[PDB]
Every structure is written in structure tokens, then in C-alpha cells.
Image (cartoon, rainbow, N blue to C red; front, side):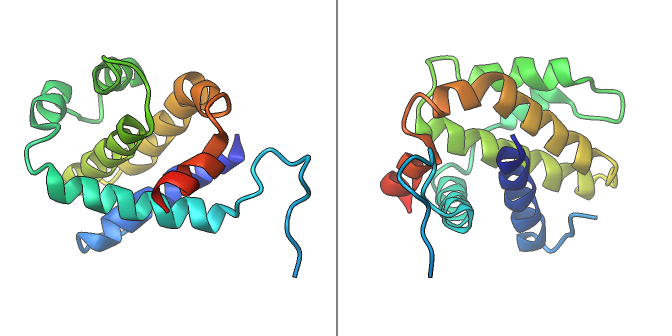
Amino acid sequence: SQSNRELVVDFLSYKLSQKGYSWSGHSSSLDAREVIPMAAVKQALREAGDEFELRYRRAFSDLTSQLHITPGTAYQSFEQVVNELFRDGVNWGAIVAFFSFGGALCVESVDKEMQVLVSRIASWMATYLNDHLEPWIQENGGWDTFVDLYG
């Protein structure tokens, strides 16, 4: 899904900019599956990832330090480490923790001067979302529901 790549890239750009860095009248019909506009998915995910970042100073330290992310890291290690964010199963709060992990991974790579990692990390996130999370999402009321719940 394109829309998921668009979510990833928006959330990351947002987080990088936030830390001072850089990435580099018609409604839907009812038969549409998401009738909620993408802008509002994005806005809600931005806010929730911001809120998640404020509650959890700690998180990912074991996870990011398990990762030891370099230009040699494969997707499979990222995947393994992300699986642990979902150890107890998928729910919307763990989806926010995932995006937030990706964001923190990006900020860390630009800090250690490995800009090249940004689009890889995004790509791993699109892949993870599409392989692993999107099937749960589209069976749990879509990003429409996520906006309902957090927006």
C-alpha cells in the first residue's frame, strides 16, 4: 500500500525536523474502506507519537541498542527487534510505538552521521507494515478507527 508508505515517510520527516534534522466539497462514498482523509491519519499519528515520546523516556534503549544499527544491518534484524514491540500482540498503542521506534532510529542514525539509513529504515517500516501490520489494521477497522480513537 502506497498510503502506508506515505504514513511512514510523513511520520519520519516530522520526527527528523522536530529534532532539527531533515529527511534528506466532496467526501468518500460509503463503499470506500477508509473514508477518513489521510491528512487526519497523519495528524493523529504525529500527535500520538509525540505523546508516546513524552511518556516513555526509557523505551527502545534495549531495543535500539539491541539493534546496533549501521549501514550493514539487514531488514531481518530490524524485523526481529520490531517483533518484540509486538510480543504481546497488535493493538493501536503498539502501532504508535513502532512508528516512534522508526522515528528514534532515524534521529539516531543522523546523529551518528549515517544519513543513508533514513530511507532504508522507512523502507523497512513500509515492508513491516505491509507484511505484518496492514492485515491486522484492515481487520480492525482501518486507519478510520485509529483516527476515531486517537485523533
